[PDB]
Image 1 (cartoon, helix red, strand yellow):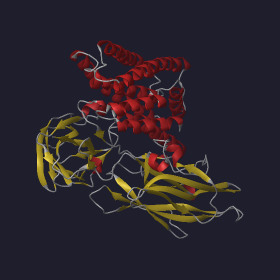
Image 2 (cartoon, rainbow, N blue to C red):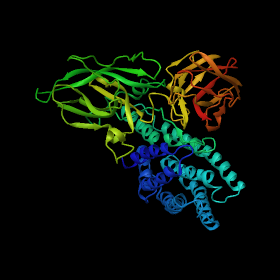
Image 3 (cartoon, rainbow, N blue to C red):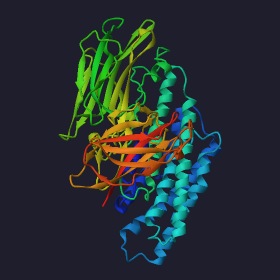
Image 4 (cartoon, one colour):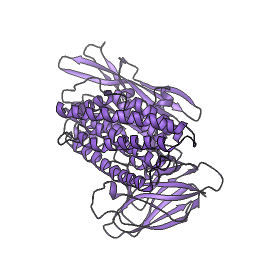
Length: 582
């Protein structure tokens, strides 16, 4: 968790200063950012190590040390420019003099040039995957650095040319860095797809650890354009992640649920929801003497409640084997599960081993009544000791605080997969990022992004579909003309605040988007074609365009409709965003 936390930390801290940040937070963000990612050789070594271990492969020592040498040089330029920028922020409008301007212009240029020059040593042929966490971390520091040209460049006495040359380069690299990072993420994801359990696990560990350090980072790049995003931005990541399965033995000797039997039943892409109920089913594992025997979690139902605007609960299929003991229900309404800690047990038999999950204790937190607690599944017979802590796989954003304020992720789903040869049950849990906001609240001071996945309702046969890898979530796909998604929205104020809508989409034809509040259309405009038929979605495939007329939140249920589709045609809708307007 050294590395995984550093990545969870940085997403958290960057969500604080995304869009146009206050020079207040921007500076403390930097002082904390250097302590995390740029403090030494040390993290950068562990970032290489991490993917080496995720891939059972190794980086040639010649290229490992080339990269490390660049990185010490960058660190020096970065430390130096942050020392400078902290003085610029402190000192007043009338100690800015021609010489303190020029000093900071040359440290910035020397940070920014040294980065361009250095990135190819994290992308060296044949080792692109193994460098991917390193690349993405530096990539981010380059883009996050580049935006202070747009904030302070006038202040620093850059002429208009130099500023606009920086901005153009920031746009191009946001794109190169995004499409590189996705491409190799997927290369190395596909090397890992096997057919055994023992391989599903690693494929998945690659998928979690890549998501936490690479994909969630790149989702924030388009928000460093602090002229498209000239206020602070309020935002969230919708992607789910799967913690390693809960077994009581490191090697199952071939009775693992197979690759195709895990991967095809984990949740397909779907509208966002919240963990509402788990129901534990419980069987008895006989021990080969009676004294080494235990009860264990054989299966379950999960009930989730959908995103705000609909209370009708989605109770699942049954997963696993039905209970011989009594059932246990844990109702989770109004609660956020921030942790799960689990006990296993096992029983050696003269030519067989049986294992199961005997106890699971969930830390939850209630922010209506700001109060933490715990709720638990015990089997009631021979629990053994904890062999599994969601903390090790999903660390805290902030260690300063106690876990119920600092947690990174909360528990959204639970599936029980069955081992081959009726030997046992494997739990697999599913997690969502804390950044999500159940209320779908539209800030009056910040630009506010709503992923269409927080709809509670699709119509006209729109579907939820696998995200292109960089949106930090999944997307909605419209193939018919008409409605497509209703999303419930909560004004943060009760005066007549006015907004501009702005929609992030990809289209095969020219189309007409239409927004409506409690049934009443308010915006209607024309939008360009961004792709051709069957193209596969890269950064440039998408597009972010304004509706003309401004409006107020006269209601809650906002509806997105579309028209101008032929046969063949397709519209992907990532996000919708509101920008307050005087």
